[PDB]
Image (cartoon, coloured by chain):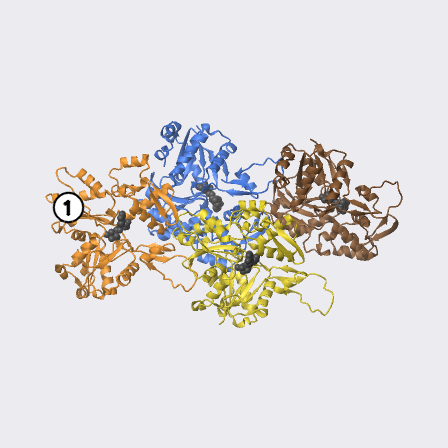
Chain colours: A orange, B yellow, C blue, D brown
Amino acid sequence: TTALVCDNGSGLVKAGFAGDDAPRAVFPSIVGRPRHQGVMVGMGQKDSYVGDEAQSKRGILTLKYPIEHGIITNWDDMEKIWHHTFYNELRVAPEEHPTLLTEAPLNPKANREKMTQIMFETFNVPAMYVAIQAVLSLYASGRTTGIVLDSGDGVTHNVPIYEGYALPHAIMRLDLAGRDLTDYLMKILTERGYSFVTTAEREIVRDIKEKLCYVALDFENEMATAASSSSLEKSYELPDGQVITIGNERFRCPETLFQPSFIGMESAGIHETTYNSIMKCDIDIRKDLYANNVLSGGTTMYPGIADRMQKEITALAPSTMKIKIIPPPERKYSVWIGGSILASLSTFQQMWISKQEYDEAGPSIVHRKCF
Amino acid sequence: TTALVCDNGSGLVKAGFAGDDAPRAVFPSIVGRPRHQGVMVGMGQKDSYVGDEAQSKRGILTLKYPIEHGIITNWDDMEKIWHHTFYNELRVAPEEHPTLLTEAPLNPKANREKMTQIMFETFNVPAMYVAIQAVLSLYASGRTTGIVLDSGDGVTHNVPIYEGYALPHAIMRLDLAGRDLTDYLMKILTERGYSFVTTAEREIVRDIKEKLCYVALDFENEMATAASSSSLEKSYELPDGQVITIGNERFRCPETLFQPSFIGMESAGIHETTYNSIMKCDIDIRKDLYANNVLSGGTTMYPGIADRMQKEITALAPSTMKIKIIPPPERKYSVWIGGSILASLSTFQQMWISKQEYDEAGPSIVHRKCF
Amino acid sequence: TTALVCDNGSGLVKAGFAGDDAPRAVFPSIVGRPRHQGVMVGMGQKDSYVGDEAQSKRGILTLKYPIEHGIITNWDDMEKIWHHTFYNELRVAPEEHPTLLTEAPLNPKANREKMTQIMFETFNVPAMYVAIQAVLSLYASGRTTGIVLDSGDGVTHNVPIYEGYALPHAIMRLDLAGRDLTDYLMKILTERGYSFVTTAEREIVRDIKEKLCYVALDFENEMATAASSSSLEKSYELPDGQVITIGNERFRCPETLFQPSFIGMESAGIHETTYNSIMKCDIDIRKDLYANNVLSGGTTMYPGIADRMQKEITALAPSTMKIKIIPPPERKYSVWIGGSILASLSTFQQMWISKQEYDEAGPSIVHRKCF
Amino acid sequence: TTALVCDNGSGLVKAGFAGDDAPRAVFPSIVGRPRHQGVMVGMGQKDSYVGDEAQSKRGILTLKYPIEHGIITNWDDMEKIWHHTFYNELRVAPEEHPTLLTEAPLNPKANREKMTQIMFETFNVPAMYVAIQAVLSLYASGRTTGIVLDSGDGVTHNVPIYEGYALPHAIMRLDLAGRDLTDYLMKILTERGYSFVTTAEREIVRDIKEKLCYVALDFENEMATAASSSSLEKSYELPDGQVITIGNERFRCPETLFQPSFIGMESAGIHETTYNSIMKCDIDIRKDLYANNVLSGGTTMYPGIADRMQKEITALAPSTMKIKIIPPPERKYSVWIGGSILASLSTFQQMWISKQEYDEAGPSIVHRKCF
Ligand SMILES: Nc1ncnc2c1ncn2[C@@H]1O[C@H](COP(=O)(O)OP(=O)(O)O)[C@@H](O)[C@H]1O
Ligand SMILES: Nc1ncnc2c1ncn2[C@@H]1O[C@H](COP(=O)(O)OP(=O)(O)O)[C@@H](O)[C@H]1O
Ligand SMILES: Nc1ncnc2c1ncn2[C@@H]1O[C@H](COP(=O)(O)OP(=O)(O)O)[C@@H](O)[C@H]1O
Ligand SMILES: Nc1ncnc2c1ncn2[C@@H]1O[C@H](COP(=O)(O)OP(=O)(O)O)[C@@H](O)[C@H]1O
Ligand SMILES: [Mg+2]
Ligand SMILES: [Mg+2]
Ligand SMILES: [Mg+2]
Ligand SMILES: [Mg+2]
C-alpha cells in the first residue's frame, strides 16, 4: 500500500512516506526564470529552476511563489513543483501510491476540484484524500480535546475540538502571517539606512527574521531599556560583508501579531481571537478547552511567545480557572506527523476516493467524502 | 569548413586558422608612404609599404595608423591591410573560408555595418561573425565566472560575467591605453636631454617602454630610493650608437594607469574602475566575482602589476573575503585562443551569417544576430 | 514673523519668503574645486565655487553633488550651500527667521537629527519645521483628496490621501529618477559616435535631455516610423560648434520610466506602482482616488506623459469608472507654493519647534512633533 | 630692493631695471676669437671680443654662439657674457641686486641647476628666480585668458592659459626658428650666383632677411605674378658695393614656417600646431581661446602674418565662432615688459629663492619653487 503524504503549505514543501518519524524532503516552493543576456554557447542551461537550485542561483534569476495565502494562483508552476517532488526528490512512481494532501479551512470550492482533477488525470493516482491541517495537528500530540492555533506562512486559523467533535461555527481565520511579518521588517529596516528591494534580498530579510527576532514579555519597559542601554544589539554579516547592527527593531517585528494595527488591519490579536473562539463554544466545555491549548506551526517558535500568550489569556479569563499552553519541542512538523499517523490506521482504509468513484461521479465527489 | 580567425586590434594583427595553438601571422598594422624625391631609375620601387616592410624601411617613409582607439578612420588602408593578410601572408583564398572578427564594446553602429559590407562584397566570404574580445578572453581559461579586465593598445574595458550571463549595465570603458603611455614616456624623456619627435622614433620609444619599464609596489619610497641611490639605472643602445641612461623614469610611465591625472584625465584608476564594476552587480554574486579576477592584454605584462592590483583591491574591499588575480603565463594571445576555441564547437555552426540572409535583409542584419 | 521656506531637493535649490507667488532664488546645488596648475599671482582667486559661479567656470574645476537620492553625504558642503543661500543670495540674517524644510519619505532617522542640530547650533534659528514634499504638493492645488506622484531628480514616491487622512502603509518609493535618465542618455549616445565622459559634459547631456526628449504614445510603431522616415531628427549646437544629430534616441530615454528594465531594475513602471498603491487602500475610496490623480515634479514635464499615463491606467482599471490626470501648468514649483501656503495659516503657528524645547529635550524631539 | 631683469634669449640679450618701460641694454650674444697671425707690437689688443665689438671687428675674427636652441653649450662663454652685461654695460654690482631669468619649456633639468649654481656662487646674488617666457608674455598685455605663440630665434612654443590656470599637457614645442630661416635663405640665394659661406657673412644674410622678406597671403598666384612680372624686385648694397637683386626669394623664405617640409621636417605648420593645441583643451573653453590669440617674439614681425594666420585658422575652425589675432605694436620686448611688471608686485616678494634656503637644501631647491 505504502501511502504517500504531501504537505504543500506556503513557502515550504514537506514530503515523505507514511509510518516514518520525519519528512524525507524539505525544500522551498519557488520557481525562477532567467533575467539577463545569456551570452556564450555549450552551457546547456535550463530555462527554469525549481527548489534549492533557484536558491543557489538566486543572484541572476527572479523568484516567484505559486501558492499565496491559501489559494493556488499558478497551476503550471504547481504542476512543476509536484513533478519535481515526485520524480526528482522522492524518486517514486505515483502510479501505485495513494497520496494525502492538506488544505486550510474556508477556501474556494474550485481549489479542491482542480487539485483532484490534476492528480487523477495528469498523475493517475489510484486514490487520494484531503484533510484539514489543524485536525491533523491534534493527532501528533495523541490528544482528543483542545483548541489548536496553527500559524504558518500564509494564514493562521483556529478551531476547537471537544472529545472528537468539531464546532464549525467557532472557526476563525486571519490573513496575518509571517510573509507580512517579513515585509514589515523590511519596511522598518529602512529607517536605519539599509535598503532591500530586490526579490532575492527578501531571503536575506527572512533569514534575519528567523535568527534575531524575539517576543518581549512587556513592550513599554522593554522599549525603555532599548531606548537607554545598548545591550540589546546583535551583528549580522551579509554575504558580501558590510556587517550591520540591529537595535530595537529586534523585538518590534514579532509584536505585530499581538497588535495588528501596525500594518493597518482592524482585526484583534491572536489572544483575543482565541478568547472569542473559546467564548463561542458551550458553557460547560470551556473549562476543558482552557487547559488544553496547543501551539503548532513555524511562526510560533519565537522565544517567549508561550509566556506572553499565557499572560494575556489569564489577563482576560476569570481568575478561578487554570490556563496552560502546550508548546511541544517540535512545532514545524506536527502537521506532517499527524498525517503520517492518520494514514496508517486500519480503520482509515475505507475512506479513500477510488478512481471508479471519480469516473462515475466526476470532480464533485470531493465535497461528499471530505472535511 | 576550416574557419578563419582574425584579430584586428590596434597596432598588431594576429591571424591564423581555427583549431591551432598560436597565431600563424603577427605583424604591425602600419601603412607607409615615401617622403623624399626619388632619384635614379630601374629600381621598380612600390608606392606604399604595409607590414614589416615599412618597419624595415622606416627611415625614409612616414608611418600612419588606420585604426585608432576603436573606430576605423582609413578604410582604404584597412582594405590594404586585409588584402595583405589574406593574399601575402596567409596565402589563402577567402572565397571558401568563413571568418571571425573581434570588436570592442560601446562602438559606433556604422563600424559593424561597414565591416560587413566590405567583407561580403569586396572579398565575397560565404559567412562571417563578430564577437566581443573580453567574452572570448574567458573561453581561453576554460572558466564560466569572473570579471575580465582587457587592456590593449587602443582602449581598456571591463565586463562581469556570472555563470554564462552577462551584465550589460556594469560595463566600463576607458580610453587610457599604451599609446598614451608611450606618448607620456616620450614627453618625460625630454627632461634628461633626449628628443624624439619623428614618427619613426616612436618605435624607439615604444621598444624602450617594452624592455625597461616596470610597476613599483609603493611609489613614495621607491621614488626615495631612486632619488638617493643609483642602483635603478639601465643602459640602452640606439641604432646608431650614443647609449643613453634611464633613471626614475623607468617606473614612472606605467604608474599613469593607477593615477590617470598625470595626463589630465579626470577618471579613476583601473583598480577603482574594477571596484565600481564589482559593486554595480548583485549583492550575492560579488563573493564569486572577487576570487575570479582575470587579466588579459598586452599592456598588462608589466612586472608587479598583479601584486599592486591585489594590494589596492584588498585595500578597498572588506577584510572578510578573499581576493585573487589570475595572471596566466600567456596574456598576449588569450583573445585569439578563445576565438579559436569558439570557432570549433559543433553548436556554434548555426549562428553564422549566411550570404542569403545578407542579400535578403541588408547590412542591418548584424545588430540582430550579434553581441 | 516672516517665516522662511527652503527646498533643498537634489540638484536644484529654491528659496524665498512665505506669502509670495514664486521662489526668489533658484540655482544648482553644486560645489567645485580647482583642478589645474594655477600659475600667475595677484588674481586673488577662491579655493571653492558654489552655485552659478561653478557653472560659469566649469571648464577648469570638478563638479560634486552633496545631496544624492535622499540622504546627505557631504555635511561640510551642505553647510557651504546653506551659508551661500542665507548670506549671499537671500541677504538675510537667520537669527530672527523661522525656516521650513522638506524631506522625502522613508529616510534614515539620523538625517533629521543632524539637520536639526546644524540649524539650531550653527545658525541659531528661533524655530524650524520639517514636512513631507508630497503632502505640501496637495496644498498648492487647493484640494483634499487625491493620489500624488512626485518625481524629481533623486527619488520618485507615491502617497494617497483621502479627506485629510494619510495611509502610511500604501506609500511606495522608487529610486529611478532623472539622474539615471541622464546617465542612460549618455550611455546610448555613444552608439552614434559622441563621447561624454567628463563631469562638466554631464551638463551638456542634461541640457539635451531637457530640450529634445519626449514621450511617445506607442513605442512599436513610433520606432517603426523613426526606423523608416527621417522626420524625427533635430540638431543641437555644442558650445564650440560641431553640431550633432539625434534620431530615435529622442524618445527612447524617457521611456525607461515605464520600462525600468532598460537599466536592470526589477521593479515595475510608475503606472503599475500607482495602480498597486490604489489597490492597497480601502474598497470604497478607490472611486474618489481614481479621478483625482495629481502630477508634480520636474521630471514629469515630458510632452505626452499625461496621455500615456491615462492610456495605461485605463488599460488596467475596470471600464466602469472614470480616470483623469491633473497636469497643472506649473509643476516645478508646486512644492514651494504649498510650503508657502502652509507657512502662513494662523493655525500652524503652534507647531513650531522652539529652542526652549530643543534645549530641554535634545535632538530626539523631532520624531515627536514631525510627519 | 631694485630687482634686476635679464632675458638671455638666443642671439639677443636684453637687460634693465624693474619698473621701467624699455630695456636699457640690447646687444648680440656673440663671442669672437682672433684668427690671423698678429704682427706689430704695442697695440695692446685683447684675446676675445664680446658684444658689439665683435660685430664691429667681425672681418678678422670668428663668431661663436654659446646658446643654441635652448640648452647652453659653452658655460665659459656664458660667464663671459654675464660678466659683460653686469660690469661693462649696466655698471652695477650684483652683490645687492636680485635677478630674474627666463627659460623655455621642456628643457633639461641640469640647465636650471647649473644656472643657479653659477649665479649663487660666482656672482653671489642675494636672491634669484626663473620664469617661463610665454607666461610673462601675457602680463604685458594685461590679460588673463588666451593662447600665446612665442616664436624667437631658438625655438617656438605654444601654451594655453584660461583665467590664470595653465594646461601643462597642451604645450607644444617646435625647433623650427629664425636661425633655420636664415640658413634656408642662404641656401636658396646660391641659385642666383651669390655665395655666403663665411660666418661673418651670416650677418649679411640675416640683415637681408630682416629688411626684405615678407609673407604672402596666397602662394600660387603670388609665385605666378613674380614669375611673369618684375615688379617684386628690390636692390641691396653690400658693404663693399656690388649691389644685388632679389626676386621671388623675397617671399619664399618666411613661407617655410607654414610649410616646414622645405627643410625636411615632418611636423605641421604653426597654424596646425596651434589648432591641435586648441583642440587638446576642454570643450567649453575653446570659445574663449579662439578669440584671444596673442602673437609675440621677434620672428613674428613679418608683414601679413596676422592675415595669413587668420585665413588658415578660420579655414580649419567651424564657421559659427569668431577668430581674431592680437598683434600688438611692440612684439620684440613683450617678454621683458611682462618680466618688469611681474618683478614689481607686492605679492611676488615672498617667492624669492633666498641664499639661506640654497645653503640648506642645495641646487635641487629650484624644481620645488619654480614653474
Ligand atoms: N526558527 C524559526 N523562527 C521563526 N520563524 C520560523 C522558524 N522556522 C521557520 N519559520 C517561519 O515559518 C515559515 C514556514 O512555515 P511552515 O511550517 O512551512 O508552514 P506551511 O507548511 O504552511 O508553509 C517560514 O516562512 C519561516 O519564516
Ligand atoms: N612585453 C611587453 N611589455 C609591455 N608592453 C607590451 C609587451 N608586449 C606588448 N606590449 C604592448 O601591447 C600592445 C599590443 O597589444 P595587443 O595585445 O596587440 O592589443 P590589440 O590586439 O588590441 O592590438 C603594444 O602596443 C605594446 O606596446
Ligand atoms: N522642462 C523640463 N523637461 C524635462 N526635465 C526637466 C525640465 N525642467 C527640469 N527638469 C528636470 O527636473 C530636475 C529638477 O527637479 P526639481 O523639481 O528641482 O526636484 P528637487 O527639488 O527634488 O531637486 C532636473 O534634474 C531636470 O533634469
Ligand atoms: N623686424 C624684424 N623682422 C624680421 N625678423 C626680425 C626683426 N627683428 C628681429 N628679428 C629676428 O628676431 C630674432 C630675435 O629674437 P628675440 O626676440 O631676441 O628672441 P630671444 O630673446 O629668444 O633671442 C633675430 O634672430 C632676428 O632674426
Ligand atoms: Mg503549515
Ligand atoms: Mg587586444
Ligand atoms: Mg522636488
Ligand atoms: Mg625671446
Q: Quadrant of ligand 2?
A: bottom right
| C193 up-or-down from D347: above or below | below
The residue to which callout 1 is attached is A292
Counting every numbered tag in the picture gives: 1
Q: Nearer the viewer, residue A21 or B283?
A: A21
Tag 1's secondary structure?
A: loop
Q: Position of residue D343 (x, y in %)?
A: 67, 35
Q: Residue furthest toward the right?
A: D40
Q: Position of residue D124 (x, y in %)?
A: 70, 35
User: Does residue D314 appear in the picture of this structure?
Assistant: no
Q: Amino acid at mark 1?
A: Asn
Host chain of mark 1 = A
Crowding around mark 1 (Cα neighbors within 10 Å: few <14, some 14 to 19, many 20+) is some
Q: Nearer the viewer, residue B97 or A243?
A: A243
Which quadrant: the C terminus of chain D?
Answer: top right
User: Does residue D310 appear in the picture of this structure?
Assistant: yes
Q: Residue furthest toward the left?
A: A284
Whether residue D316 sits left or right of residue C187 in the image: it is: right
Quadrant housing residue B61: bottom right
| A303 up-or-down from C343: above or below | below
Q: Position of residue B40 (x, y in %)?
A: 74, 67
